[PDB]
Amino acid sequence: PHRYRPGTVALREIRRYQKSTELLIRKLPFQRLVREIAQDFKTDLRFQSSAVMALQEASEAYLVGLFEDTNLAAIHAKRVTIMPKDIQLARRIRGE
Amino acid sequence: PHRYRPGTVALREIRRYQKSTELLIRKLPFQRLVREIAQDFKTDLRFQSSAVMALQEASEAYLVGLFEDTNLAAIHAKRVTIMPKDIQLARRIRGE
Amino acid sequence: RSRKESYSVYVYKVLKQVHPDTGISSKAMGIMNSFVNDIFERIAGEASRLAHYNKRSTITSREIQTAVRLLLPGELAKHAVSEGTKAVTKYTSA
Amino acid sequence: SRKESYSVYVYKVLKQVHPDTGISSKAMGIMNSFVNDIFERIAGEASRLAHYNKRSTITSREIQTAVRLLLPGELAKHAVSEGTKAVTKYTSA
Amino acid sequence: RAKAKSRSSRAGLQFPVGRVHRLLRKGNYAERVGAGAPVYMAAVLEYLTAEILELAGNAARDNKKTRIIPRHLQLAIRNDEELNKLLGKVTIAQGGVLPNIQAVLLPK
Amino acid sequence: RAKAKSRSSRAGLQFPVGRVHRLLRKGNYAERVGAGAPVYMAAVLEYLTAEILELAGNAARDNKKTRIIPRHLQLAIRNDEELNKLLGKVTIAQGGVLPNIQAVLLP
Amino acid sequence: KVLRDNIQGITKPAIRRLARRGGVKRISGLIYEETRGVLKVFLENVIRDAVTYTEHAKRKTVTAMDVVYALKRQGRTLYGFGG
Amino acid sequence: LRDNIQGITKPAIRRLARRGGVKRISGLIYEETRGVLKVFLENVIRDAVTYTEHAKRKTVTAMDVVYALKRQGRTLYGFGG
């Protein structure tokens, strides 16, 4: 048998996702999430497809930047695995 | 030979400095620091005394906020003592 | 002499409605003046944008209202809206 | 039913720097967002400088100062050099 | 001429109305200011002013005082989550900070 | 009657000047706009435009292309501290990110 | 019809992929939930402002500019969808 | 008028740290702190100078400091505004 070890692929994927430019979140799911949120404030709420995409890229960019800081926090803590508290520290420092 | 243990006084100072509002940095020193920096842009420059104070309060406010985040980072790292790196992490997360 | 404007007189009055028996230091007053000018600029600034965005030359109670909703968070934003909406309704009725 | 943009000017600039390079419509759309963002800021600051100093007119000086406040390091500088010239020259042109 | 009357009183406001009407036309924010614009705004500025002063006044009372000082404004703003945010970037001269000490720093 | 002549030509610029003048006097930036302001500004916008495009063109070549795409703009900006700073908060569609991996994650 | 639980529409691989792009090598099982609870706040803030702008303009359909203004208000600008 | 960063005394640094809730301070903090404070001051002072210069003045006023701070996401209340 043959396979890669844990972490070999993870590093590979880091390279690859940094490299590519596409969306990582599925579109219809994201679109629906937007509407599900939107339906709280009001009904008769419609979106242009360009508005949804604009939201999606901003949303992914947000999370990715958050993960970069989260990762650093995990490293600061001398770890590889990120945990909810590494996210929380990063956010807190940001002032969220 | 009575003594108060390590940390008893440190906490005391924290209490007090959080409570009070006065400037902690000596004035003539601070004022001169401003000028030394200023002279690197321009000689024969002047300041209103209120301008120097305005700078000093903002400067202290900046550092205190920085120290709060630094402290959290040290705690995240399971440590009471803050190290230069904890400052660096906090700054980085903040976009510096 | 040149003359300067502030809200010091109006701040005193407001203080009396919340705390009829209390005063205010000159510094706290200076701060409240810095505060009012800050909030004013923001709302007016955002209202400016709304007028621009929606192709207008005029700021009305709505541009003020929307600016309030965008700038103020949660419920605080609401009371400001309620009071403004009313004040206009009332002004023309008073 | 008509819009305006800087797409035509951006295209030309690309040639001044890279004569053999083309550009996507999106890259152009991005450059358009960029130009409008910078424009608004400088104009915003120039307004303010005039306001702070209690004035009605925006001059090349307010633009210059605004550039410095917004741009960091050399970008601020090269921009000032170029702005100064364009005005100096336009007048003599 | 008919008797002149102050508008602040008229709108049930303490804050000036004619002036706000005016200030809204300055800085070049909009060519024109609508009649209800300053009325709406004056009410807002007054409301927010009251909220800060009330909370600060409570702080003054907590400290057994008869007035508000910069510190009380700071405590008031920060304790109130929504004002804390509205002015979350604001540095208050002589505001000090809230007395927040991390539990991990304390002994048993 | 003198012939109408574009100011951009006069100023040696590619960006429009009359338009910039037009935009500056409105948007409510000021009651008045001086003659040299639009000109100064047009030069600035043009300068910055060139810097981004130049670097993007280089990124395009790093990718062996003869064209600029959103990605090349991202790479151009983030490998230049001053532009990166100016636009440090800008999200560029399909811009992507830099391939930075921390040493501590490697074998 | 009303929608629901589309927070799960953000699938596990999707979260991991984002984390990986960010340089995250290894992800704790609780991150998925923790991450969603943060994404959600971000979306709530942006969408709401976009709606607020949309309503001010007295429209029903949200356009790209409404989103752009909303994101600008939160200080994260976005290029290529207008400006 | 040189290395006046040393005019920021060690206790002065520690007290700020204390106010921030810092209980223990590494011996290498003093220098690191200075390398940050200085940058902060450099950015604020310079903008104030820029405003002062624009206005054709020599004396930096509180207002010029306020504008410098303001734009960095830091309105300061108390000196006018």
Image (spheres, coloured by chain):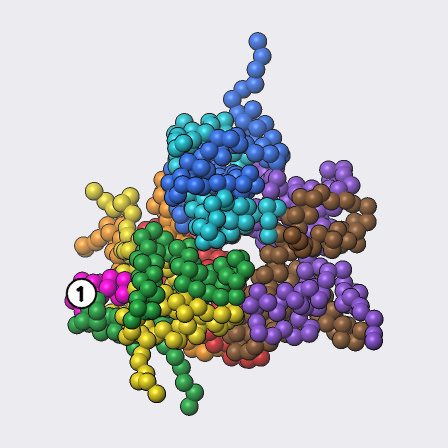
Chain colours: A blue, B orange, C green, D brown, E yellow, F purple, G cyan, H red
Residues F22 and A87: in front is F22
Q: Is residue D72 left or right of residue E11?
A: right
Residues C47 and B58: in front is C47
How packed is label 1: few (under 14 Cα within 10 Å), some, or many (20 or more)?
Answer: some
x and y, in percent, of residue E90 in the image: 39, 62
Q: What residue is shown at x 62% (from left), y 52% (from top)?
A: D33
x and y, in percent, of residue A45 in the image: 45, 41
**The C terminus of chain H appears in which quarter of the rendering?**
bottom left
State which region is magenta.
E49-67
Query: Tag 1: residue type?
Result: Arg
Q: Is residue E55 magenta?
A: yes
Q: What residue is shown at x 69% (from left), y 64% (from top)?
A: F19
Q: Is residue D82 left or right of residue B64?
A: right
Q: What residue is shown at x 39% (from left), y 76% (from top)?
A: E19
Residue indicated by mark 1: E61
x and y, in percent, of residue D78 in the image: 69, 63
The relative height of residue C71 versus residue E64 in the rendered view (above or below) is above
Instruction: Tell me if residue B39 can be seen.
Output: no
Q: Chain of mark 1?
A: E
x and y, in percent, of residue E53 in the image: 26, 66
